[PDB]
Image 1 (cartoon, protein in one colour):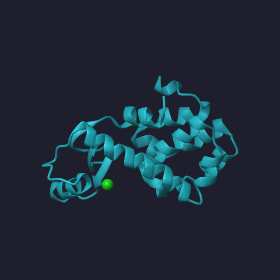
Image 2: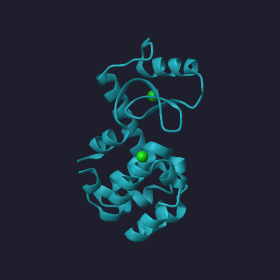
Image 3: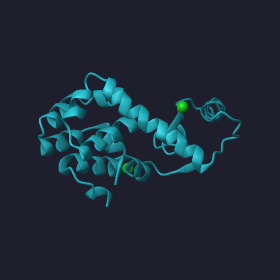
Image 4: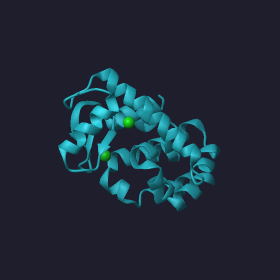
Amino acid sequence: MNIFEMLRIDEGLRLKIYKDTEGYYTIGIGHLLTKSPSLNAAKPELDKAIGRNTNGVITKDEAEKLFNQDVDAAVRGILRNAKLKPVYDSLDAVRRAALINMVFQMGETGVAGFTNSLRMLQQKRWDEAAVNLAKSRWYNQTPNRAKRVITTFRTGTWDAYK
Ligand SMILES: [Cl-]
Ligand SMILES: [Cl-]
């Protein structure tokens, strides 16, 4: 198991514009297109992302290409973030994947916002960090995915995904 297979299980794959759990226009492997309500504001963002007139549908290859970019950008965002970087550096390889997953879903700003949990992770207080991460809108809105991520932070193994 690796970050790619982990996010592929959490986000699924859809070749046609769809709405995410929050109601936003998305395509492929969790690639957010726009927070705007218009499918007309979404279609152009999609064409611009792919480099072609797509008419709202893309191929598997195109989806995977957006995915590689999005994972690369998540990592690079963590490393440029003054609050995230020190946490990431402190972690083992499995748990680093868990932080990348959070960043991919909620963005760097959001994650950097979990001040207390981040401090607990850095101190390696696993059980306490898992309890604090659960007290969030994130966990209440997407409980099954959140529990998988949380379990990965608590245990440091890929069990929740096996
Ligand atoms: Cl893009
Ligand atoms: Cl869920």
